Image (spheres, coloured by chain):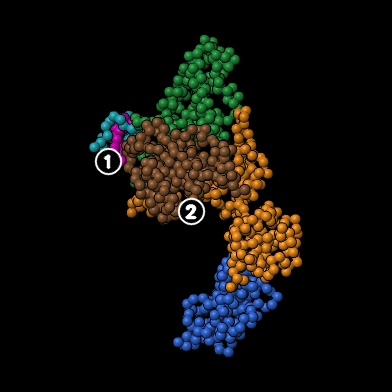
Amino acid sequence: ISTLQVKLYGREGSSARTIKATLPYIKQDIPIVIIFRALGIIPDGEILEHICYDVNDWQMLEMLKPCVEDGFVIQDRETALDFIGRRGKEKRIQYAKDILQKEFLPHITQLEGFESRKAFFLGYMINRLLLCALDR
Amino acid sequence: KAIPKDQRATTPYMTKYERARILGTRALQISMNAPVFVDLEGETDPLRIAMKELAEKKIPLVIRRYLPDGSFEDWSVEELIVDL
Amino acid sequence: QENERNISRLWRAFRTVKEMVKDRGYFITQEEVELPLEDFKAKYCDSMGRPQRKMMSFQANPTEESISKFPDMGSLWVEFCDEPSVGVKTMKTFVIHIQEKNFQTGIFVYQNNITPSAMKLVPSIPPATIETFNEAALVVNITHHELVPKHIRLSSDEKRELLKRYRLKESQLPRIQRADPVALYLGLKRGEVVKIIRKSETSGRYASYRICM
Amino acid sequence: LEPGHAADQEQAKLIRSAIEHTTLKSVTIASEIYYDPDPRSTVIPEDEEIIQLHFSQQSPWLLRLELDRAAMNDKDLTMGQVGERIKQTFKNDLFVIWSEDNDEKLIIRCRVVAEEDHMLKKIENTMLENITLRGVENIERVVMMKYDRKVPSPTGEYVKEPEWVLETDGVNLSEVMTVPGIDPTRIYTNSFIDIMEVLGIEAGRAALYKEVYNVIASDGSYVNYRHMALLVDVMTTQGGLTSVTRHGFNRSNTGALM
Amino acid sequence: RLVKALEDIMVHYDNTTRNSLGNVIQFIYGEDGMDAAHIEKQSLDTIGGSDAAFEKRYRVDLLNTDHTLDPSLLESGSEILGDLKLQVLLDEEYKQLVKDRKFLREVFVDGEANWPLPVNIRRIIQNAQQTFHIDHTKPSDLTIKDIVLGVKDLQENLLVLRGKNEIIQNAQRDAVTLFCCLLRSRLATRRVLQEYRLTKQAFDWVLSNIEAQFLRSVVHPGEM
């Protein structure tokens, strides 16, 4: 029984409106872009495609810009899992790569051949969150 | 130290608590077959006898009223006014 | 624009200052307090329009009526500063001014704020007392308010009399804060008891007492 | 209100307009950031007349505010008020233009006087939050409620003299009572905290009693004065406002067992 | 919480409301030293009404042949007309009533007259004009001095505090100020002679009864 939380930092008025997430027994909260890149979806836009299911929605994407600004440091999968592992030498990746299978959203699958499922689902949660944040 | 009989500042009237305490004490005394200083006139109840003994001011007791500073004024039951 | 508002606020602050000083037991005529804005502008404002703030700073003298009760009460000096963020620089000038002029009470009326480096040397010149006051905090006389009863600063003999008649100790009196706006208004030192005379819906007049700490 | 103008609600509206808080964000439809190179010729065809009339060193990045025409009437303020507010806020490091109220488009243009594009955003942020067009802070809203009042007639008796009183969602007594136009001697707030902080411990006592008594009498009940007076006095004798909790009177210098 | 906070508070034998530390909460309990049980809502009919009605109801002018006491009211109303020495006392009484009107209108700014006070005077008066069976068509055997100086001396007996120093006496006159306003308002010469039509005996009985009930109404020391 695990509980995943997706937090939207910075209220109405703040400029640092980043979006982070809480993963099972991991020290600090991780930017969502890092999570997506740790799941295989590396470049921008495709992440937004996994989040914003309508390219016409400029508001939601505008709200997603500082998330891209946040996770601009990590530009590949290996360093993403390395980041999560640093939170929690290469062993940490195998630690990280375990948490995304056995602990991160276990209700879909605890296998190893499913990464796009949890990615799209996470993007769905982001979509709901922002829909609530945009007063829609 | 003490407080002189003159220049006493407290109420010359007996408080209801003083009355209840005095009647209670005197009734406690009478209840243990102590001498009665008034005519019974048929009365047998120690409290009632104490009341009649109070109306005639025949109760040899004295109230020590304590001021918050530690001072105290003495007021005999015979002197205190009972208007209650 | 901003000029008229500044002039008006400073004027009301000045009136309130006069009321305060005359309430502490100093000689200020009632006519002086009720100084019209036209006269104020025609006595303190320049021909250009700039309000010369330092032109207002005056001194006050204790009435003989006040000397009878408080003989040790000396002359007071009101000072309206021109500098906004007053640092230690003007503070030295004011302190040395009260020092040389040899007064007992110095009222420093600033218009914004005082640096902690300047308030570090304010309570350090006995027996003289220097009191800091914000101009915006004196625009309206708080003692004129409904819920504010009259406080009467009584002498040491009156205080000892109060402590004797109710056979009290200083810790048994009701207390008033030193930073209490009324205590600040009267300029109360620690230990100074005030007789607060309030109206009562059950007796009409009721006198409480508050020792300052 | 002032002892003079009592029935003049037209002045009460002015006081309401001078007290009720009003931010720039509260009257803004939207904000945009354009790249407008030539200052004397705008890409937007709607701002051509504006820059044409404001003719009689800068930044290419433009900050364009669009305001709500209906909200400018509610708060009762002009474009000049807003523009001069922004100007007085940023002084010299922000060139500000705007359209007159007669136009059908309430627009404001702002320019700064590397990495500058994501530096103007913060500015507009501070333009939305940390900007007060008029009124006092915390004072979120003000309502003109006409109270009935018993006043001694010149002939002697008491007559109902109704006056306009300004109720308020929000509290900032330290700056509202110093406002020119109202009677600062009768001003009151349900927050006995602010009363105690501004007017003194005695006024705090009076307000505290007023509030407790208000709670009691609101139910339709009635408790004799001396009881509530005793409570308030005990809450107020320590010098400040002592609560009736384990933090208040239980921290007093009484007996340990008690 | 309320109980545990106000627990150790009671009235001591100097009518001072204190705690276990002896700290003064109220110098005079309830600011008047009265027990709440012996307090009833009574109207202060001087705080209301026009100045014209106030004058019409309280002004006695022995120097005026129109605003004087009719010989039907007082037994000595004929030989009282024009008496300067008594008009001094009446001017004193009326002036005190005016001062009381000012004071009351300062205290209760809304002009409320009905306020809880000890000793129901109305019931005492209506008991006077019931015990002695006084008719409304007979000259009272009272005197201006009797009423004025009588009431003025009644206030000296309405004791709550009983010290001998200036402070305690000031607190005493402060604590009974309101009730004395009520007393002067109800026991004014015009009101006593015309509205009540009390006799000397009945008036003395009223004074004695008022004093008694006042002394009964005082809070008992030890009252938790």
Chain shown brown: that is C
Label 2 CA crowd tier, 10 Å (few <14, some 14–19, many 20+)? few
Give the label on residue B32, or none.
Answer: 1
- Say which colour chain B has: cyan
The picture places residue D52, in percent across and down from the top left corner, at 74, 61
Name the residue carrying label 2: C85
- Say which colour chain A has: blue
Q: Could you tell me the amino acid type at mark 2? A: Ser
The picture places residue D80, in percent across and down from the top left corner, at 67, 55
SS at badge 2: strand
Q: CA distance from mark 2 to mark 1?
A: 85 Å
Image-quadrant location for residue B19:
top left
Chain shown green: that is E
Residue B72 inside the magenta-drawn segment: yes
Q: Which residues are magenta?
A: B63-81
Residue C151 inside the magenta-drawn segment: no
Q: Residue at x 40, y 31 (%)?
A: C65
Q: Could you tell me the amino acid type at mark 1? A: Met
